[PDB]
Image (cartoon, rainbow, N blue to C red; front, side, top):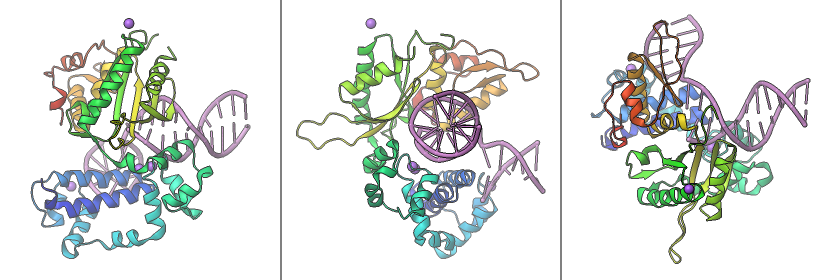
Length: 327
DNA sequence: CCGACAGCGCATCAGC
DNA sequence: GCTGATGCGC
DNA sequence: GTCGG
Ligand code: NA
Ligand code: NA
Ligand code: NA
Ligand code: NA
């Protein structure tokens, strides 16, 4: 629905969510507020009272009260107060830097480091990830047009195949469901040589090649199975340079690849439904495998999965195009 | 009433 | 030095 | 903060 419908309420709950996560370090309250904000964001009527809102799953007594105060006064005293709070607002803000979580943000503010400028001034107090996060603070908050995602995909698929044409790489996330923009790029990689029962350089060789053609520009973390870093499309020679983007690359055993593609394609709501449906059919589906459940609930050995559809077939679901997995 | 609310890789800390 | 915990991100 | 065993 139009954001003007209940935007004031959903904005309020999202702000409350952020303070719970970043300042109070109450992750479950953060999630409670987010869930309330989502269910309301989807509600196709302008809410007139807290009681009305309380009918929606995830909206309880306290949020109903807050909605009543917001409807009557156009604000919430508690939120107004924390907004103006120098320490709390700075803590909340610093967590926007990738690599600075609630613990680091609190420590920085405790010692008088409150702004990006302060961070810029205190490099030796930042770890590698945090320096990269500061360096690209603005770029990381920008979204990526699908057209750019397509150019990025072109490069990733090309270089992967160049390293070894037996690699399989899939760009997942909402991009794969056809979204018009992305927050970052999520690449799942496999190779027939690598199974759950079977090399510690399969990922490295790919990351290296992407660095050699100057696509990958920085590394946040790199192990044998997961890479997280930064990339940038080549500039059109005279055109303004593209923003640096977050890209993750994960190596997954071949026998677990398609479970991974399904999972990381989502959406999150689709995943919940498919997993439920799988249960009532006597299957357990997670990120890695689908397994049968015996009559007393004992999980059997993972079943053979050679495609996304193999998974749909097990639980008697008709195959669903990623474009159709909004829920 | 009171516990669940996901789980795991990687970088780094804390303890030995 | 080694192991396990913690912070962080997803 | 909300849900539910
Ligand atoms: Na409710
Ligand atoms: Na952060
Ligand atoms: Na953040
Ligand atoms: Na080849």
